[PDB]
Image (cartoon, rainbow, N blue to C red; front, side):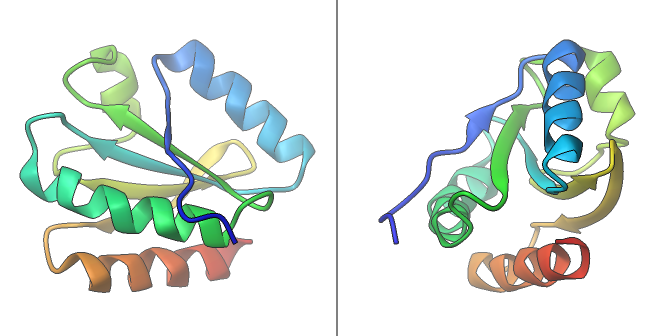
Length: 119
C-alpha cells in the first residue's frame, strides 16, 4: 500500500457539495478532518490519518477543512465546536463523527470503526 495519502483540503461549500455529489455517484463515503493549523492535536493526528487514508486508497477519499480558513457557514454546517473533529459523510450528509481529543492511535481505530459502519 502507499506509505501515506495526503489529505485534500476543502475550501468552501461549493467544493464540499461537488465532492459529495461525486462520492454519492460512486457509492462512497468521504472523511472530513475539521482541524486548524495552530491545533497541536490536529497536526499530531495528521500522519496517522494519512496512513489510514493509504489503507483506503481508491475506496474512500480523506479531506481536511481548516476551521479558521474556510467560510463560517461551512464550519457551522458541520456543527463543529472541537478540533480535530473527523466526520464521515455519505449520500450527501453527515452520518458520523469522532472527536480526536484523546490518544491519536485510538482515534484512528475509532475512525476505522466509523468507516466500516458506512462503507
